[PDB]
Image (cartoon, rainbow, N blue to C red):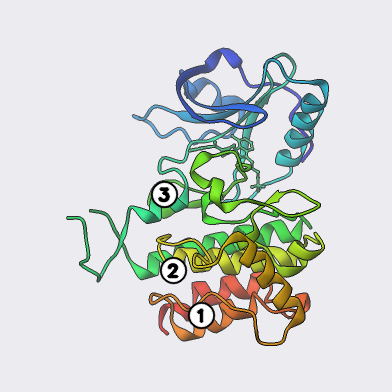
Amino acid sequence: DGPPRVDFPRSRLRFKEKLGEGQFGEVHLCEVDSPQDLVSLDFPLNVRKGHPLLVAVKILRPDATKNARNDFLKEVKIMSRLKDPNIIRLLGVCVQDDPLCMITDYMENGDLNQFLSAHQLEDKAAEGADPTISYPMLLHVAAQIASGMRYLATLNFVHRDLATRNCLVGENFTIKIADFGMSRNLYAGDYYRVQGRAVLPIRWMAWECILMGKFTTASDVWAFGVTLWEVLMLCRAQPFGQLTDEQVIENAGEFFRDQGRQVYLSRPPACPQGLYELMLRCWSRESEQRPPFSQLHRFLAEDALNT
Ligand SMILES: Cc1cccc2c1C1(CCN(C(=O)c3ccc4[nH]ncc4c3)CC1)C(=O)N2CC(=O)NCC(F)(F)F
């Protein structure tokens, strides 16, 4: 659980592509040369013979301030603690000399938002003639997100920014939860200045997060309710897309006032009624009435398939 004491061989990382940016610096796609030497010092790489081993590297700015440097190593320690199939896992680090590095698996299919947008629901031939996804598989995607968040809750770890844009897709519809920050141009519209505070993902936020700034596992459940909606809409629309950002903030006030003026996300066509009612409980006014991730996961893996 402690951070690794010996660095990954920096010289083995060979650059291919830039994957992204951030205030910290860049994330690179790298190839690991002769990876069969290194699994012997695991570093549990999933070397599949006959295939090149690709890897994502989060790299600290070479011009980084001392405080950003400090923050980067704080994250190394946070990431070192996270050990679950549905959470981004640290393969290795490089911190006993510059540049500072965190290394993780490569997910071939990028973020879940862009992946679902490219798919048509199966039975619906409103196609591009073009990738389809079955309803069982939609559910399987959602179940994996639920299981990852359930793991994070056992750690008393609060994510604060769960959404499909922060989920990565590997082979066979496998999912991992990540945390990109909010610099990607593609999702600039998912973040808005809350007065007297910070730029935040208001459309995924529980009312107590918007009004007061209280983030907890129960607010993570609320964000999952919104994330599940996304998945069952196949990411064709932003939550509360009719409403302006200012209206979204006003709507949080109406949840608090609880007088029937608030509005909720409606039921996606792909979502059965039983699953919609569970979805609704995620948005309960009282935190303690929101469902535990254990319940959410069990329903998605079992009951939602037949109803
Ligand atoms: C690369 C890297 C290394 C260490 C941490 C992190 C990362 C990242 C950097 C941002 N990032 C990417 O740009 C990216 C893009 C496309 C990709 N295809 N395959 C891999 C890959 C990676 C995702 C991975 C991250 O988001 N985090 C934060 C975290 O996952 N926190 C864990 C939690 F979500 F549970 F809170």
Residue type at numbered disc 2: Leu
x and y percentages locating residue 151 in the rendered image = 68, 58
Separation of marks 1 and 3 at Cα, in angstroms: 24 Å
- For the N terminus, the image quarter is top right
Q: Nearer the viewer, residue 206 or 92?
A: 206
| Quarter where residue 256 is shown | bottom right
Q: Which mark is residue 152?
A: none
Q: Nearer the viewer, residue 204 or 177?
A: 204
Question: Circle 3: is it few (<14), some (14-19), or many (20+) Cα within 10 Å?
Answer: some
Separation of marks 2 and 3 at Cα, in angstroms: 14 Å
Local secondary structure at mark 2: helix
* Residue at the spot 60% in from the left edge and 42% down from the top edge: 180
Separation of marks 2 and 1 at Cα, in angstroms: 11 Å
Question: Circle 2: is it few (<14), some (14-19), or many (20+) Cα within 10 Å?
Answer: many
The residue labelled by disc 3 is: 114
Marks 2 & 1, CB-CB < 8 Å contact:
yes
Left-right relation of 96 to 297: right
The residue labelled by disc 2 is: 232
Is residue 54 placed above or below 148 in the rendered structure?
Answer: above
* Residue at the spot 25% in from the left edge and 70% down from the top edge: 124
Q: Which mark is residue 275?
A: 1
Which mark sits nearer the N-terminus, 2 or 3?
3
| Quarter where residue 91 is shown | top right
Residue type at numbered disc 1: Leu
Local secondary structure at mark 1: helix
